[PDB]
Image: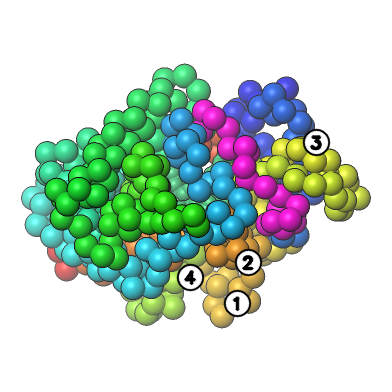
């Protein structure tokens, strides 16, 4: 069993061994089960063949009880999944993307009044609080100023628990019930008319969604799925720190971004999402027997898809281990060579419905760091570990000497 070794190698567990064996897939005993791990753009296409792979019963329970909730969309298949997947997608169109980005820009500009007056600032902690406040307000979720940091911290505890053992895991195990109870009482009050809601906002839509059979969701399940909107928005803080880390370690692109328009911002945001580690792998079950790449996939066998490795596959990317935003200058867009938030199509599979929100928030945030403030990056540990899942520059990225422009 290599579950310990998985934990020790993190984002490199699959890549190391495909490189070693010179095969795009190998067999391994993980999580007590039998696994096929696989990597590469063609592997991803097989992984998103929804007649060969299912998600029901693929998500480990420890991950359900901390990061994501029990029996949510991640584990649904078939038309039941497509039905609920459209709910999420209705809340993440370009309209909502523009709105979340505008709100973030509004919050960054106000932050300047406080940041100028402070000595240092930890970008990760600022990001968490601003995203939580923005996510709740865009969602219609009441959020008192005094609970903002506490609710954002519970969201990050959930994110940071899925890939952990021991104390780091327990934080997520205790945050998830706090958050589900909070949101569930909102859902109940919304259904009673005791809390004002607004058609088209996330809280309202989750509270009143109807399934195929026309029932509403359990208040707890509505709470769970609303939390699967608020939590990932707060988790964008990881990407926003990696964005600033990129500018610092590759400052040649700061003037490249300054004098360029959104073309350069778009490319930069993409290379951040490609180059830096976030989601290591995805799980699924072979739902019926098949053969691919001279290997037999027996039914009920668990399979991992290597997201990190595919994003650094030299077959798909030139100098993949180097950070080069210029690789996106009017480049063919495939759906399986870059999969940091999944591959395929989001309405025909499990690909992330909030990719657009993730990118526009990143663009607005990047625009704020480049055009709106000057700052120093003082002596600090900027190391991020490929063994910590998720990963983050150790210090949270400290900024000092912040000044308006
Ligand atoms: C911030 C960084 C983010 C990363 C790294 C990320 C990554 C992912 C990945 C890898 C998946 C699963 C792909 C699959 O199962 O095939 C996923 C699914 C999902 N994401 Fe994200 N995502 C992010 C942001 C967001 C945001 C901002 C939202 C909402 C506003 C969101 C909502 C969801 C939902 C609801 C699912 C479940 C999709 C399904 O099972 O059909 N995510 N994400
Ligand atoms: C077989 C083990 C699989 C472990 C990972 C399963 C799924 C991971 C990605 C889910 C992303 C959901 C949206 C973003 C929210 C977040 O990152 O917390």
Residue under circle 4? 267
Q: Main secondary structure of the magenta part?
A: loop
- Residue 349 percent coordinates (x, y): 60, 59
Mark 3 vs mark 4: give the one in front. Answer: 3
Mark 2 vs mark 1: give the one in front. Answer: 2
Instruction: Indicate the quadrant where residue 368 lies.
Output: bottom left
- Residue 401 percent coordinates (x, y): 18, 52
Residue under circle 3? 27
Question: What is the distance, in whole Å, between disc 4 and disc 1 at their CAs?
Answer: 10 Å
Q: Is residue 388 visible?
A: no
| Discs 4, 2 touching: Cβ within 8 Å | no
Residue under circle 2? 335
Range drawn in magenta: 46-63
Observer-nearest residue: 292 or 163? Answer: 292
Query: Which quadrant: the N terminus?
Result: top right
- Which residue occupies 16% across, 38% down? 147
């Amino acid at each position: 069993d290599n579950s310990l070794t998985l934990l020790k190698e993190g984002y490199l567990f699959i890549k190391n061994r495909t490189e070693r064996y010179n095969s795009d897939l190998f067999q391994a005993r993980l999580l007590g089960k039998n696994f096929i791990c696989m990597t590469g753009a063609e592997a991803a296409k097989v992984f998103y063949d929804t007649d060969r792979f299912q998600r029901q019963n693929a998500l480990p329970k420890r991950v359900q009880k901390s990061g994501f909730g029990v029996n949510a969309i991640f584990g649904m298949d078939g038309s039941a999944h497509i039905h609920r997947k459209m709910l999420f997608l209705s809340l993440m169109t370009p309209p909502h993307q523009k709105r979340l980005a505008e709100l973030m820009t509004e919050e960054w500009k106000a932050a300047v009044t406080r940041w100028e007056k402070a000595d240092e600032v930890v970008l990760f902690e600022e990001a968490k609080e601003i995203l939580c406040r923005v996510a709740c307000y865009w969602a219609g979720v009441p959020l008192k100023e005094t609970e903002v940091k506490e609710r954002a911290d519970d969201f990050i505890d959930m994110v940071d628990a899925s890939g952990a053992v021991g104390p780091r895991h327990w934080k997520g195990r205790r945050a998830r019930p706090r958050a589900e109870e909070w949101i569930e009482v909102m859902i109940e009050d919304a259904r009673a008319g005791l809390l004002k809601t607004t058609s088209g906002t996330a809280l309202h839509e989750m509270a009143f969604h109807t399934q195929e059979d026309g029932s509403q969701l359990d208040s707890r399940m509505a709470a769970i799925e609303l939390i699967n909107v608020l939590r990932p928005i707060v988790a964008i803080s990881y990407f926003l720190v990696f964005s600033a880390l990129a500018l610092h370690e590759h400052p040649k692109y700061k003037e490249w971004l300054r004098s360029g328009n959104s073309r350069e911002r778009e490319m930069f945001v993409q290379e951040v999402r490609r180059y830096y580690p976030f989601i290591p792998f995805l799980g699924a079950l072979v739902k019926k027997d098949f053969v691919w790449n001279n290997c037999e996939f027996k039914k009920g066998t668990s399979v991992l898809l290597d997201l990190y490795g595919t994003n650094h596959d030299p077959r798909l990317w030139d100098h993949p281990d180097e950070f080069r935003p210029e690789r996106f200058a009017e480049r063919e867009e495939n759906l399986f060579d870059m999969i940091p938030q999944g591959g395929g199509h989001a309405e025909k599979g499990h690909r992330c419905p909030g990719e657009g929100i993730t990118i526009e928030v990143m663009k607005a945030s990047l625009d704020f760091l480049v055009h709106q403030i000057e700052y120093d990056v003082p002596e600090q540990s900027l190391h991020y570990s490929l063994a910590r899942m998720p990963s983050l520059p150790e210090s949270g990225f400290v900024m000092s000497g912040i000044r308006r422009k």
